[PDB]
Amino acid sequence: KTFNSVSKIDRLSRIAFPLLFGIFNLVYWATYLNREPQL
Amino acid sequence: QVQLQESGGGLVQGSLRVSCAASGRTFTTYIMAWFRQAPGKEREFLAAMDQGRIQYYGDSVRGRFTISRDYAKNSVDLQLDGLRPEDTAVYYCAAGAGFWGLRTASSYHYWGQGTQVTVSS
Ligand SMILES: CCCCCCCC(=O)OC[C@H](COP(=O)(O)O[C@@H]1[C@H](O)[C@H](O)[C@@H](OP(=O)(O)O)[C@H](OP(=O)(O)O)[C@H]1O)OC(=O)CCCCCCC
C-alpha cells in the first residue's frame, strides 16, 4: 500500500503565489500613488 | 504612443501661424496650451484653450497672439502677429488637465518636440 507524495507543484506554489502577489502589490502601489503633481 | 506634431515656419523677417495636431489620444476634454523657451530662460506660458472654447493669454503676449482649437481634427493653432525681435525662441505645444496649474508647465503631461522661431531685423 503506497501513498501519494507531497505535490512539488503545491510546494513551489506556496512560495510563488504570495511572492508574485506581493511583488505586484508593490509595483502597483509604487507606480500609482506617487503620481499627482506637486508645487 | 501619444504624440503631438507641431508645424510652422522657422524664420521670418511679420505674421506666422503654428499648428499642433494630437494623435493617439483625444484631447477634447483636456486643456491645450502653448509655451515659449528662449535661450537661457525658463518656460513661459503663452496661451491656453479649454474644453468650453475659453481662451487664456499671458500678459507679455496679450492682444497679439490668438489661440484656437479645432476639436474635429483634434488640434490647437496659434496665430502670431506683431512679432518683435526678442520673441525668438522654441515654442512648445502641450495638452493636459490643469491641476495646480493652467499657467505652470508642471501641470501638463503631454508635450511636443518644439518648433524654433526666429525674427530677423
Ligand atoms: C505552477 C506550475 C509549476 C510547475 C512545476 C512542474 C514540476 C514538475 O516536475 O512536474 C510536476 C507534474 C507532476 O506533479 P506531481 O509532483 O504532483 O506528481 C508526482 C510526481 O511528480 C510524479 O508525477 C509521480 O511519480 P511517477 O511518475 O509515478 O513515478 C508521483 O506519483 P506518486 O508519488 O503519487 O506515486 C506524483 O505524485 O508534472 C507535470 O505534468 C508538469 C505539468 C506542468 C503544468 C503546469 C501548469 C501551470
Image: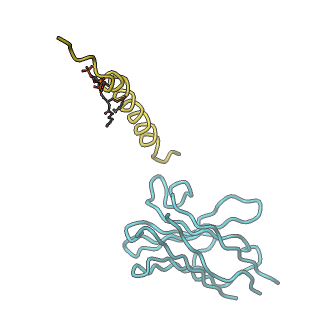
Chain colours: A yellow, B cyan
Give how far across and how far down residue B59 sits, in percent. Answer: 59, 69
Q: Vertical placement of A10 versus B81: above or below?
A: above
Side of B86 where A13 appears, left or right: left
Task: Give the image quarter of residue B78.
Answer: bottom right
Q: Horizontal placement of B41 versus A21: left or right?
A: right
Instruction: Note whether B13 is above or below A24 in the view shown.
Output: below
Q: Residue at x 56, y 80 (%)?
A: B19
Between residues B40 and B81, which one lies in front from this camera angle?
A: B40
Q: Quadrant of the C terminus of chain B?
A: bottom right
Q: Work out whether B109 lies above or below B91.
A: above
Q: Residue furthest front?
A: A1
Q: Name the residue rendered at 46%, 78% in the picture.
A: B69
Position of residue A20 measured from the top left corner of the image (x, y, whole percent) = 39, 32
Outermost residue, bottom direction?
Answer: B14
Residue located farthest toward the right when viewing the structure as drawn: B121
The part of the image, by quadrant, that contains residue B50 is bottom left
Q: Ligand 1: which quarter?
A: top left
Name the residue: 57% across, 69% down. Answer: B93
Q: Residue lying furthest top in this view?
A: A1
- Which one is in front, B51 or B84? B51
Q: Can you give x and y, in whole percent of width and height, for residue B56 in the image?
A: 49, 70
Q: Which residue is painted at 53% across and 80% down in the image?
A: B77
Q: Position of residue B4 (x, y in %)?
A: 54, 70
